[PDB]
Image 1 (cartoon, rainbow over the protein chains, first blue to last red):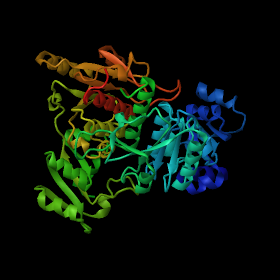
Image 2 (image 1 turned 90 degrees about the horizontal axis):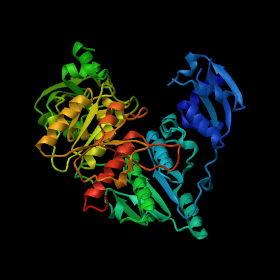
Image 3 (image 1 turned 30 degrees about the vertical axis):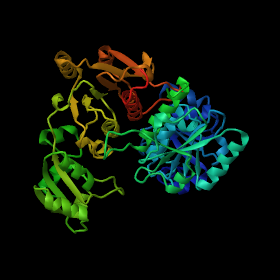
Image 4 (image 1 turned 120 degrees about the horizontal axis):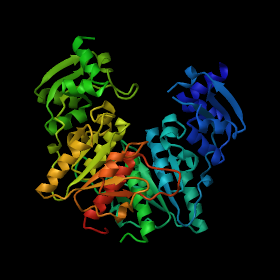
Length: 257
Length: 267
């Protein structure tokens, strides 16, 4: 199976994904979110029994290929889509007065990427930016842990932090006064003393190093989650979730107070 | 592949093997140092025998009074996350009793209970958040994912050793202990988490002694736990579609308890 051997290396490495302009998505529910949100499904691989899976086959008019149970078990899925990777265009992320965004600086864990995508999506954020030497958004561990939120929350990989600022300066020029907000071990202020009712990009650092200093230079404010003591820290996705929850709380509350 | 080796290897599989031997593996200088610092007995220390041996490893080896064994480096590839951290040192650490009295209960009690977790990574992450945010213990209910699973241990980032984590088979033993705490003078409330909870998390009074119940990743809290809840709370969501990972939810709800406690702003 020649087509299959192309599909198996789509899981294995970033290099071949981005040469083919596609990636693998598993599960009836995530695939349905992909279709629902406009992402082209080039191929749709299926085992040759569930009600949802059957409904997908006669609603999604694309290349439909039946598969042996042996071959589908590679990581077990009943349906698997080959879904079109879209360009890394920062204007895919909508920016309005209530702008609420996340920037993940140089993440090493794809699991953390997908996880923050899920939290950003559930808690009302409008986009994610994966800046710098990163693990790939379209890694299977990221896709999986997004739990389909990849498809509703636009996640843009942007090599340089310079290209991010140019898109930030431009939203500023339009009227939305985005403010860059770093997280720190050395936090200026408690997260709950800061005003998340304003257009906000939230900068979150590597799991093992902090935010890069260069990201700290561009940061207008810095916030910290108050901790119990000396040798305690939060996983980046967990910390990002808590801060997003605080932003939601203030916006609903109409105040910090 | 000594008979001893195979016994240590077996500590990576089912929870029962660890339990009956009363031990589990802890990998990495940093986690082992934290086990030693918080008084977890170390039965054996395995180190790399074709010796790199950093300053840290050397320091553990001449300070930790225990059985010490040089191991071929490929036996130590034993457990890693293949092509992610081959351990230079591994400790065989004693498992403490699953006794709820290891969790201290004061007037401002904040505890977490994780109902039959599917993912050991989620357990360790919650242990880490609870530790960092001032909770006083975790209970893990059921015979699903294990606190002492290598992924949990690893996820906790050493917090396992400072945050008392106790396993119970089912809700009965937990309610026994809770009713005893309330007779002594701490009116602990059970607070479940759910999507469609009775009130938003920021409208709940988290200053009160609180046992927070986090449900399983796909099935949520069991019917037995919902029946036992005094209250139910939820994090408000943007749409009908998405949801939160259990550990992420737990972290946010623990943070909200911290927020209301320090100085006391709302609820």
